[PDB]
Image 1 (cartoon, chains in turn orange, yellow, blue):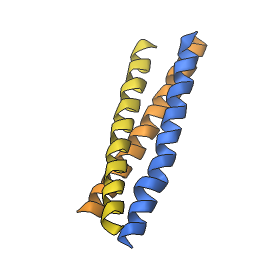
Image 2: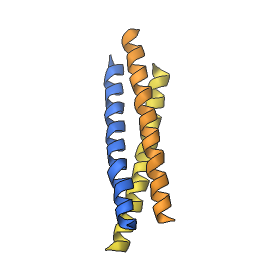
Image 3: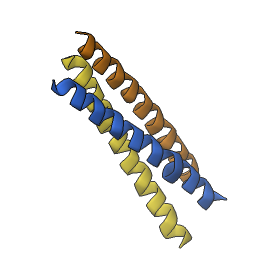
Image 4: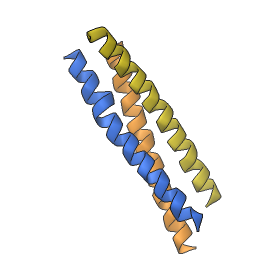
Amino acid sequence: AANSATAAATSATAAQTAETAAETAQAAAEAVIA
Amino acid sequence: AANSATAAATSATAAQTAETAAETAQAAAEAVIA
Amino acid sequence: AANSATAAATSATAAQTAETAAETAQAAAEAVIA
């Protein structure tokens, strides 16, 4: 399942990048508001 | 991988929720400034 | 199969969320605060 493994790795990388972007966005928004 | 796909989907949902929160905060700031 | 399609969709959504958060959530909020 090389194709499935590559898809899983890409999905995990995208998930990590999205989570990091979301956390910085929320931190910046709450810092600006507060 | 089904587990990887589910993790990617839930991470995308969390990122979308955080982005909506950031957009709401930005809209509130824009209403204040404008 | 559909694993590649969902991986690509998740990657695109993560990239869009990161791009939106970089400018609208951080740069814009900093602009209002400055």
